[PDB]
Amino acid sequence: GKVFERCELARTLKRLGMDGYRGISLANWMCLAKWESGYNTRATNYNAGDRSTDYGIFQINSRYWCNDGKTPGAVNACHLSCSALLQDNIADAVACAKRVVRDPQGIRAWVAWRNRCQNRDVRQYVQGCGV
């Protein structure tokens, strides 16, 4: 797919109801989506340890969320192919991201968030977007 521009994405995420979903602010979703993919919807990351792979803009993991047909002991939570998470339309990626935080860990499941966003101010990511 395509790569999102910061405000291009804040508008899209706001539109899809990401502002305050399960408490997460648009800004933490934006911090998440940068340090996980650079807004690259087509982003992919392989995990040699468990053979899983993180897909799309919010790097949804293949081991428990979507099925990519090659992950050991894969659970298919969102009950969808991981390919769907690599489209220009992120509706599908947003829904698994929403799902992921519906669990106990919430936003903290993503290692990149805990390292770059957690315990920091993230208002920058949205400053200037007008949302």
Image (cartoon, rainbow, N blue to C red):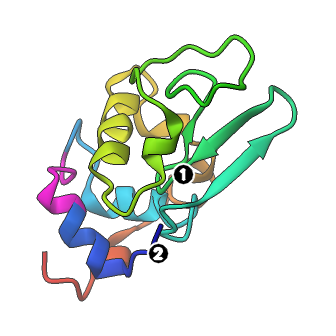
Q: Is residue 115 magenta?
A: no
Q: Is residue 76 above or below residue 10?
A: above
Q: Nearer the viewer, mark 2 or mark 1?
A: 2
Side of 16 where 3 appears, left or right: right
Side of 96 where 72 appears, left or right: right
Look at the image and give the residue range highlighted in magenta. 13-20
Residue 113 badge: 1
Which residue does the image show at 21% across and 83% down from the upper left?
129
Dominant secondary structure (helix, strand or loop) of the stretch shown in magenta: loop
- Give neighbour class at mark 2: few <14, some 14-19, many 20+ (Cα, 10 Å): some
Report the residue marked by disc 2.
Answer: 3
Q: Is residue 13 above or below residue 95?
A: below
- Residue type of the residue flagged with mark 1: Trp
Position of residue 131 measured from the top left corner of the image (x, y, whole percent)? 13, 74
Side of 60 where 14 appears, left or right: left
- Residue type of the residue flagged with mark 2: Val
Q: Quadrant of residue 75?
A: top right
- Of 70 and 19, nearer the camera is 70
Residue 86 badge: none
Q: Is residue 41 above or below residue 55?
A: below
Which residue does the image show at 32% across and 43% down from the upper left?
92
- Of 27 and 64, nearer the camera is 64
Which residue does the image show at 40% across and 75% down from the upper left?
4
Q: How many marks?
A: 2
